[PDB]
Image (cartoon, rainbow over all chains, first blue to last red; front, top):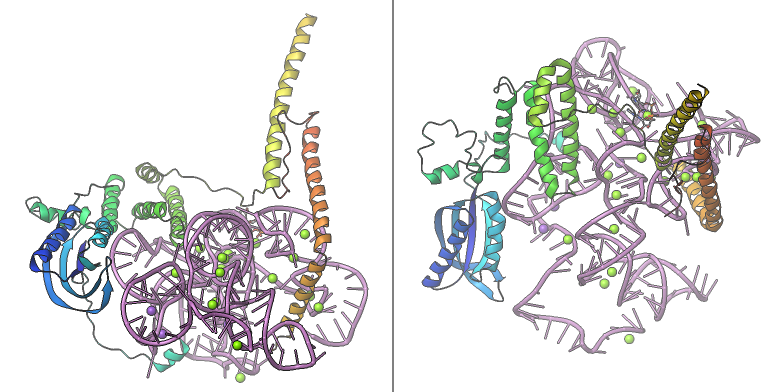
Length: 118
Length: 171
Length: 71
RNA sequence: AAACUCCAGUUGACACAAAAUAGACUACGAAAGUGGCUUUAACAUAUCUGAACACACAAUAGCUAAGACCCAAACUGGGAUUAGAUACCCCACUAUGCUUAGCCCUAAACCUCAACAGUUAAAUCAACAAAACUGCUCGCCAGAACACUACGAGCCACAGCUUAAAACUCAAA
Ligand SMILES: NC(=O)c1ccc[n+]([C@@H]2O[C@H](COP(=O)([O-])OP(=O)(O)OC[C@H]3O[C@@H](n4cnc5c(N)ncnc54)[C@H](O)[C@@H]3O)[C@@H](O)[C@H]2O)c1
Ligand SMILES: [K+]
Ligand SMILES: [K+]
Ligand SMILES: [K+]
Ligand SMILES: [Mg+2]
Ligand SMILES: [Mg+2]
Ligand SMILES: [Mg+2]
Ligand SMILES: [Mg+2]
Ligand SMILES: [Mg+2]
Ligand SMILES: [Mg+2]
Ligand SMILES: [Mg+2]
Ligand SMILES: [Mg+2]
Ligand SMILES: [Mg+2]
Ligand SMILES: [Mg+2]
Ligand SMILES: [Mg+2]
Ligand SMILES: [Mg+2]
Ligand SMILES: [Mg+2]
Ligand SMILES: [Mg+2]
Ligand SMILES: [Mg+2]
Ligand SMILES: [Mg+2]
Ligand SMILES: [Mg+2]
Ligand SMILES: [Mg+2]
């Protein structure tokens, strides 16, 4: 299915950041993934301090990887990200653009009698 | 299971699907889909192999095939999740619902009942006549009563030869 | 509502648990003896079967198991 | 008071424990239950009804074995109150609550409302609860107490569970 990898990388110089992204995208391809896009969300201060691989981090590079992969690739990829020392935090979610939003007419009231009795 | 390269049931009959890039074929195959998509291909395979009209999904045959695919999925689930009582319940309920369908198909269309059993690999079994605990006292006694019968039968045959032998001597 | 029916059952169960506690060693000796007789009564039922069928001894290789022991 | 004083405060490092707010929501699941995040699998049945015992489940407590252990905590020890002992209060700590693999099979397991289908016109209807009913099916009931008992039987249960009487007694319950 289509997945979205939310990737927070250690704050590094441009050469090491490109090497980490290439090494991360190749890991996806080695597991059968078809990588669709790579987005840079920018380097920013983390919302809180994160300890990863015997180091403390206060800033990180936020990246997204939109890709398709077999369902069995997720478990294997999650294991790969846990061992990469340049990855602060990596999470794989089902791509939000796959879920189609259902139309909403509006807010129908709920009767007070139902509130109490229910 | 169908090969992973198999296309999804929705994209198998679109014109020109055989000339698209290999990447596009992977994205429309079972490899890139959830297991529920592989089960739709299995159901369609059984429907064309067994039923006379593969597009009649409301016939008793199609329901047995659809439910048989679900039963196999639960068995595969429980092979990996052996303490999942919720899915163990769904399996046992699904097996019972299929038996009720097979009973009604056997009673109405035996020729189709036979093709369903051959096609799906189902060995129809008639239910036991009585439901009662076979406890230790009964299990032991029933075993003894069968041994006693077996021994009595042997003795009754050794009382046929001796009588036969003595009768011949008189002559 | 009132709980008077519950209270009667509460006291009955309390006194029963209290009686069982006081006599749990006598009750254990009684239960053991009953199980012995139960095993003997079972053994007789099986012996009756082969004897009424014309056999003089138990079927060859048959040993009546102990189906009432904790083991 | 005892206890602690490798105590307390700040800062940093740091979980096999538990999951603020959302939730004024009333969803999911057969029920039991389920409210941190992600992913995978996944929520029976195109007529209904259908079991103390068949089949599969079943909070809390508890058993067996091996682990974890922050905090909580039967029990136990100490301090205190007390005429004094136990409890209520304080401190410490254990079984246990957790994980794993087996059991045990209970609850005020209760919306105290059996499942399905139908009706809102008749009389609206003992009372209260929760407006009053019809069809159909299964389960169950027939004064109180004896009695969640005795005996028998079955059960991995052994101070256990399930099923479940009678005698004596009363004119009530
Ligand atoms: N006992 C059977 O094996 C059996 C077989 C066919 C039909 N039934 C039907 O089951 C109902 C219950 O009969 P009962 O009152 O004599 O039994 P019961 O309820 O007194 O139970 C006695 C025995 O019958 C079994 N039993 C109970 N309910 C059953 C059911 N619905 N179906 C099958 N077995 C059941 C129990 O497990 C036990 O072994 C009746 O409608 C009967 O016609 C029972
Ligand atoms: K929370
Ligand atoms: K809340
Ligand atoms: K209640
Ligand atoms: Mg009493
Ligand atoms: Mg002091
Ligand atoms: Mg039914
Ligand atoms: Mg019955
Ligand atoms: Mg039932
Ligand atoms: Mg019960
Ligand atoms: Mg339980
Ligand atoms: Mg436990
Ligand atoms: Mg503590
Ligand atoms: Mg402990
Ligand atoms: Mg936990
Ligand atoms: Mg409850
Ligand atoms: Mg019912
Ligand atoms: Mg009135
Ligand atoms: Mg009575
Ligand atoms: Mg009880
Ligand atoms: Mg009892
Ligand atoms: Mg008994």
